[PDB]
Length: 364
Ligand SMILES: Cc1cc2nc3c(=O)[nH]c(=O)nc-3n(C[C@H](O)[C@H](O)[C@H](O)COP(=O)(O)O)c2cc1C
Ligand SMILES: O=C(O)C1=C(C(=O)Nc2c(F)cc(-c3cccc(OC(F)(F)F)c3)cc2F)CCC1
Ligand SMILES: O=C(O)c1cc(=O)[nH]c(=O)[nH]1
Picture 1 (cartoon, helix red, strand yellow):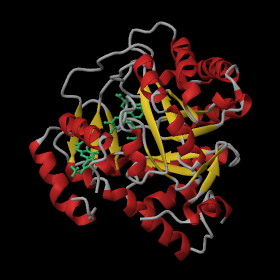
Picture 2 (cartoon, protein in one colour):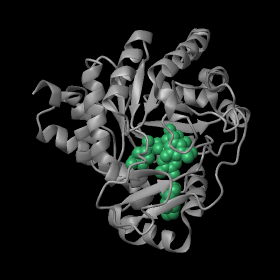
Picture 3 (tube, helix red, strand yellow):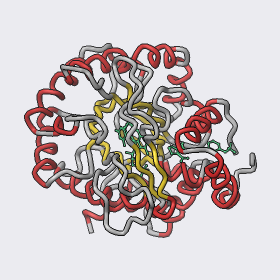
Picture 4 (cartoon, helix red, strand yellow):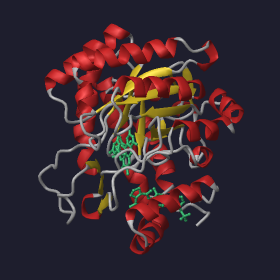
């Protein structure tokens, strides 16, 4: 329980929990427990990384989606994450798609979800983050940054304005903002990844960002999908360097269904995450890193469940990594596991630290 044993959670607790609660109910309880600190390894200098104008004591963060409304930020740092990202958050509140909208594929160590941006909205999250704004300031100074993921409302008419509003309301409370334009569960959202659309969108976002006071000015990253054509990637890389985008989050869930999936629910509509997404995600990181000449910070996400998974993404070009689906299968202990294996792998491979491994595959 509080001891935090990897086998117990993986073999007994998590399985029992999922055998009694449906996916969504399990998630809601997860958020509750985390917010209350009902949770079960010391970071070494080796895991420290410096990017996006911040210090990160460890490169392992919790991907967007687990804490959509910023209700468990502190319980997440306590879980061992080097940084937390909340969202996606939409300007106005919205319920998202009807239940069921999340599905487990245990035989594939994967999950499929079609939430549709269920969100409390900017205001609610704004006040929720303001209530701990000073505490976060100290956490960030301590190497524990906060990122905020921005989405857009379903009935919105001006996609750009939606993100612009998010930048104005939550940008002052975040170390970095994420323009999420890769969600597969919102009609026409991914089309915003197009060159022309993306350029107009990011130009406005960055302008709103630059208009904020210095200490409240966040880095701006763009979260992309793993289903982009070689053309989309070239365009995104071009726009990113043209506008000075601070970084990229690679990748979101995939609408593809790799041959081999065994889960009974493999044909449910939605974005696929977990092991089946891992390598497709690592390859997207490898490609974007090269297209940006390794000058644009990348946060690798997609099927990370071990130190090896984390290091392959770092060697492919990621400065930081995130995980989510792995947490839903192995529980809280997975965080320490990934960090411990990552450290051992770095030493075992001759790297003085994480910073030394970033992009290493491209130099060999
Ligand atoms: C239930 C669920 C909800 C998610 N919600 C969001 C979201 O609101 N915004 C976002 O940018 N990504 C969201 N994601 C995507 C994750 O942040 C991540 O990009 C993806 O799942 C790959 O990581 P993983 O294999 O470790 O889960 C969600 C994923 C899941 C499984
Ligand atoms: O589970 C799923 O299918 C899905 C999601 C999910 O949110 N899972 C999930 C869960 F159920 C439980 C904990 C958890 C959190 C803290 C302590 C803990 O330990 C003890 F309970 F002991 F406190 C256990 C973490 C999780 F990540 C997202 C959609 C699919
Ligand atoms: O809320 C969602 O449907 C959602 C958003 C996103 O960016 N990715 C995902 O897999 N689901």
